[PDB]
Image (cartoon, rainbow, N blue to C red; front, side):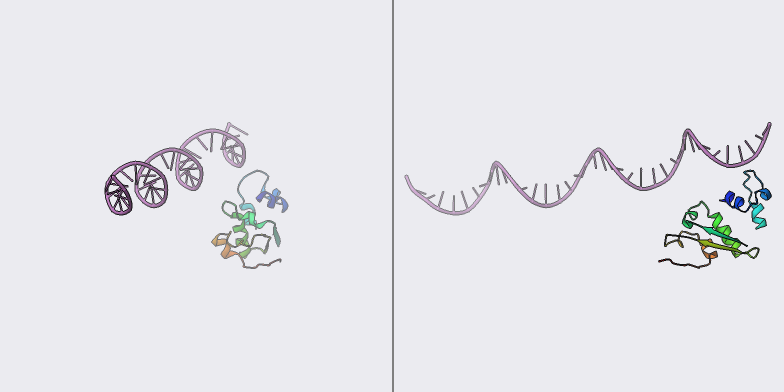
Length: 96
DNA sequence: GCATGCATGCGCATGCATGCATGCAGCATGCATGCATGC
């Protein structure tokens, strides 16, 4: 996911080409909109690091970020940890 | 030449499947006892 984010933003020249795990190059540098298909799968990651960072930068006062998620499960609220749930703006749209 | 990240091998905990036994209740059977009945 980090590789795709870097490549789509065309910052690999700025960040670097090697496999180095440091991501503070983007994080320190970080209007861009995010679209997340199959949002439920991201909640099954080891620590939900990407979701937490996205919610943090959304709640931060550095740059404007809009987050849009798509889900088929009706229980997407309980699949999130307490911290991200608190930092998640409870904006839900239902398509029936 | 070195660092790094990935594939692999092994240990550990756990849940589940299997073996194993014992106590109870029902039933069938054989015996003890009561009854009839004649001589």
